Image (cartoon, rainbow, N blue to C red; front, side, top):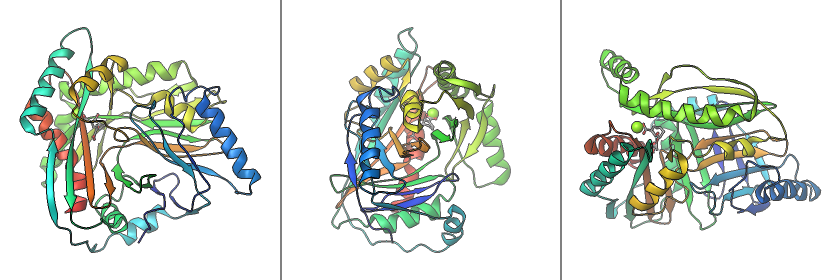
Length: 375
Ligand SMILES: C=C(O[C@H]1C=CC=C(C(=O)O)[C@@H]1O)C(=O)O
Ligand SMILES: [Mg+2]
């Protein structure tokens, strides 16, 4: 299985692994949408260093945190290795062995009543003109007795989530950021780009007809359509100023994960160039699916209600090459592991039609993707 110091990315676009490490890159990604920002200038330079030093076709991979004022977890590997997503999906339709793991401690940060009161405050605030949507999140901390094998976990992740954007990111503190993301934030392929934001959620059902009825009810739910509209209206505005052309559908489609129905709107467009995967990714992130709307207002509520720092959770994860192509997906349905400690994360968009218990339960089902991976 995959060694923990290797990047792994599984996607219908480009799926690959990396090896070794040429140079790390931790410049904060704030203002990274401007080609004249320190982030972009330093990026170009390192790609230049890489080629001079004889790195062929250098790639920048890893993760950027929710608040891009914080350092990035990005690097250029010594080498990378394509593989076929399809071959990997076929190989994962198997019984997936598991690491025997003992729990020494488990802890919900916060616990149910506290989270419910947080949702109620945020909901009440969204009832005022001051903000329209706040994304609130919570964690499950688990401590084992043994170092966790991130490679065995990845095999389970893939087997349980063969379709999503599956990532395994080595981290500078020795940890691994692992996950099964359903949300494309930015793909760039030549001059064209796309983004498939999600927001609005309904639990899958084992019964075929009930499953379909759950999806249908989601498309008819005013709360979830409102939650989703605030996201797409935001990104449409942002991308208007920046794209030669832009296609956005007028209503969402349905997408599934193993646990959830989601509302999804596909954006496609042509990039003004002098643009790359990261200039556009930093432009968009975070959307109101992960921060809220208006952005700065929502991030203030988040800072005042959440009893923890998100760090990489709710950021983006992916890759950019020196030609400006790349793909960035939202850092959700995911876990940070280091030695015998795991932190799982989930958020949910809060609007005036949000109930405290409903969003505790929605974040619960979101947490279940990684809880399933761990058993
Ligand atoms: C913040 C998360 O999801 C976002 C995107 C998909 C569904 C979401 C929702 O319905 O609240 C969130 O906007 C998460 O999965 O932890
Ligand atoms: Mg939601």
